[PDB]
Amino acid sequence: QSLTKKVWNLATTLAGQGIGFTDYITQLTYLLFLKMDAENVEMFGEESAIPTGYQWADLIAFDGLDLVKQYEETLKLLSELDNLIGTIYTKAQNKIDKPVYLKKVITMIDEEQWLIMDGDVKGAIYESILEKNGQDKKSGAGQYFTPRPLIQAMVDCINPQMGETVCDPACGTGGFLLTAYDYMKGQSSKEKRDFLRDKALHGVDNTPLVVTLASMNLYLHGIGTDRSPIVCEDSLEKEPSTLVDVILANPPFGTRPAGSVDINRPDFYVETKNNQLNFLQHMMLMLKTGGRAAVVLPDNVLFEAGAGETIRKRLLQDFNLHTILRLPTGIFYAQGVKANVLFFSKGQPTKEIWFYDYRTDIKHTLATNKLERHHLDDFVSCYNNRVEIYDAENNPQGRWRKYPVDEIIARDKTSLDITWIKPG
Ligand SMILES: C[S@@+](CC[C@H](N)C(=O)[O-])C[C@H]1O[C@@H](n2cnc3c(N)ncnc32)[C@H](O)[C@@H]1O
Image (cartoon, rainbow, N blue to C red; front, top):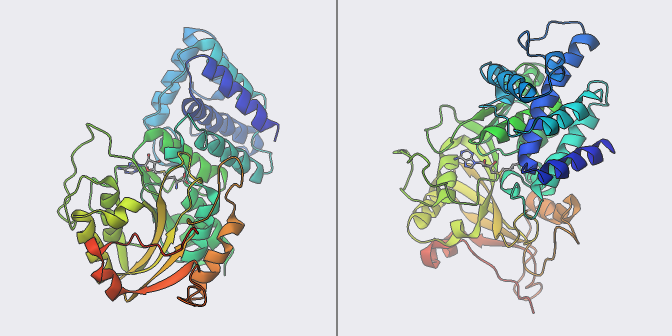
């Protein structure tokens, strides 16, 4: 709030040098955590945990190639540490080679009092910064972000409860985990208030800086003290060591980058190069019996022949794919995206699949008619009240329709890419 504007103007200035928004924001985060540590030494007494010689006061004293060297040394030592600090500084790395322009970020962070602010305030500034980068049409940070309105509706439908484990195995900025924690925190303790605190959440992302942003975000909203729920791993690489109650995820829509290690997963139902089918497999394999998932996936997952069908067959047999939400265009960073939310539990077969079409004749964009949480109110009510809106003769254009599993098994390729609403 005016602090946000100052953060945004330093962003364009570094952009003026060769320094992009995502890089700026990681360096801002590295510096912010360090400053806040120092503040906590005055504001509440105790000894720092940051090594001696590398605290905030040591940093601000240098100016030249010397400033850049001290900063880099500082990031090296912190990355070597454990728990929350080590997570914030995961494979930490300076991207600002220019002393003058680093000193500007340092100087801006130094001049405020971060501990003291309303605490909600730090959260909301950070969420606001993450979003403005995330919906930046030519910055491509949207690959690291999901719109909050949609996360909220998903968490509301899944309805996580105190005592459950929640995992997002492709966590980006940590929005699902942040929202599921807020949802659970306001419910009726104490083995379980402590469970939420220490044991409920887990997030995985393979990209170091994104782990830095996620672990900071969770921390700035009061999630954790000395430990982070976020780990830096490649989810597809390894069979999961622990099964969970709830999965919440928006996995990458893009291909696995070239030169990434080849995966070796005998536990998978089928070998495929489709990155999204593999995330879907990995997540099905991650659930406990009785567990449930809500996951954002592309249309391709619903129609693709070969491996896709094999997996959709497995999904119908051993899981209850009770709900598919068809998402509108114009809500993700890179619009065009044809996406869907699939909700399913593990154990029981699918007998019926309820479709909610929020795509056909729906018009959102990032600049005008923005998606907000109230647009998914009807969906959420349908989710809870399993009474068909569609009727062949009374309401053929109704958004909520139930299909028995036998019609789906009878479709070509076992396709789940079903619509029925005439645009006309
Ligand atoms: C669309 S983002 C998730 C956004 C998140 N829902 C939020 O609140 O910001 C997808 C994430 O998956 C990560 N990712 C890509 N490949 C991965 C992999 N193999 N293992 C774990 N994470 C991966 C990306 O780095 C990216 O942050």
